[PDB]
Amino acid sequence: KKLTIGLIGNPNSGKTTLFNQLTGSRQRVGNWAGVTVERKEGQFSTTDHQVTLVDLPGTYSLTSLDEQIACHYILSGDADLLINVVDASNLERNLYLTLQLLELGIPCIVALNMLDIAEKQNIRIEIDALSARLGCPVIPLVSTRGRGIEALKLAIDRYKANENVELVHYAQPLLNEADSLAKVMPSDIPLKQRRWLGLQMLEGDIYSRAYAGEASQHLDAALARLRNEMDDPALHIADARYQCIAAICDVVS
Image 1 (tube, rainbow, N blue to C red):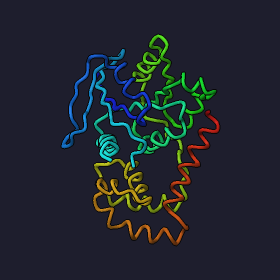
Image 2 (image 1 turned 60 degrees about the vertical axis):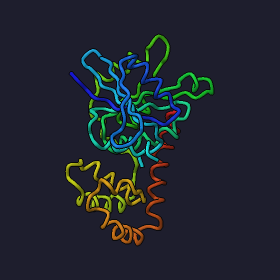
Image 3 (image 1 turned 180 degrees about the vertical axis):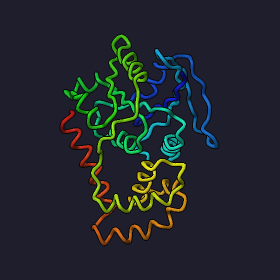
């Protein structure tokens, strides 16, 4: 059976290296539609699947051209699953991107990279505790004898919808305002993603408005409403995300 998988992580996080390991010489260099950014695709197989792997440009956040490409692809829904390459030696910084994928609700597998760099600086990562808090599998990419890859291939064959765990705990009125923005958005987009798009707009993101159809004319009204209910809506959003990531890292690292 054929799956298409998007490969996503921070720049400088061993993403290209995983890409080459997975695909060997079975890769095509193309170009992202309408821009001159290079788009790599590659092929590998698993026990049950033939996999088309799409390397997305490194990015720290879904919220320059590169960043925008990753996000447009993530939101296009073309991919069945995403492989999220995470630097174990910079967990907290790297999970900011992971959180957005999970909030978007896209099937995810976290390939925990740079174990050897982590080990070297006395950082150990509690794999199952991370996995429980994310609601998606976490696969240590041991480089020794291709073990990591084999285990990743196993995870791919066993992939499923993420566990619907609570992630960031937003103040209710932000959720409320996001719900309101969400119901006036193009319905071709899942409710979960519509809610996420609303949340980004409230925090002040401009690229998100592009997918949200009508919503952007309701935003100033939404924001004007919110500022009666709290002192800094966008900062409360920043604060709840950080709260969530730091509570994870405290247990996990």
